[PDB]
Image (cartoon, rainbow, N blue to C red; front, side):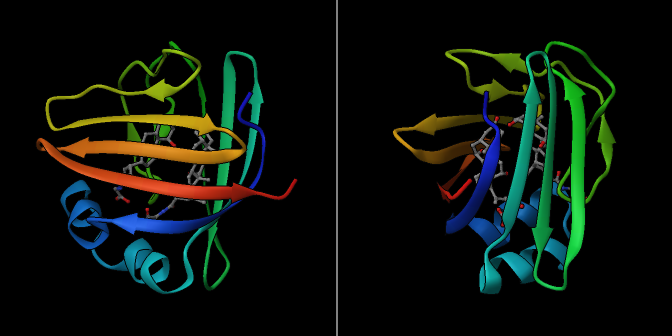
Length: 127
Ligand SMILES: C[C@H](CCC(=O)NCC(=O)O)[C@H]1CC[C@H]2[C@@H]3[C@H](O)C[C@@H]4C[C@H](O)CC[C@]4(C)[C@H]3C[C@H](O)[C@]12C
Ligand SMILES: C[C@H](CCC(=O)NCC(=O)O)[C@H]1CC[C@H]2[C@@H]3[C@H](O)C[C@@H]4C[C@H](O)CC[C@]4(C)[C@H]3CC[C@]12C
């Protein structure tokens, strides 16, 4: 149950990480300067995050954890894989991608891998 409103303030390897994944400039220009917000909603197996960035564009995804072909990017591009829970933390696995998504303490903490190279992110809640 990841639900809430969270503000980000940490980006590590950000400009290279988001390019490799397939952001041209759109989300990364907004993240480096303004640092992204979100509103999350989890209904057991069913999941939704909605994110918002500087000019007040929305990007959402809605998927069922352990189900496939409903999951989409910061840009909102759809993909097919199996999102998995392990210790209550959400992960996908790909040839080119991996990541893991969790709550530590009261703070929200994410650690990600593309092409074998690492990203990590940090956020504070105010729901
Ligand atoms: C507000 C931002 C948005 C990320 C973004 O779009 N950044 C562009 C960039 O990284 O440059 C992040 C910070 C940490 C994220 C959370 C962490 O992964 C932990 C936690 C993981 C859950 O599985 C789903 C909700 C969420 C709260 C995540 C939702 C949302 O994703 C958050 C709270
Ligand atoms: C940073 C990556 C990818 C960004 C990207 O590929 N952008 C391409 C584009 O913008 O064109 C983000 C975007 C959306 C994310 C997924 C969606 O938010 C849904 C899902 C949520 C769980 O916390 C973790 C797994 C999972 C499945 C997320 C894994 C990391 C993804 C795939």
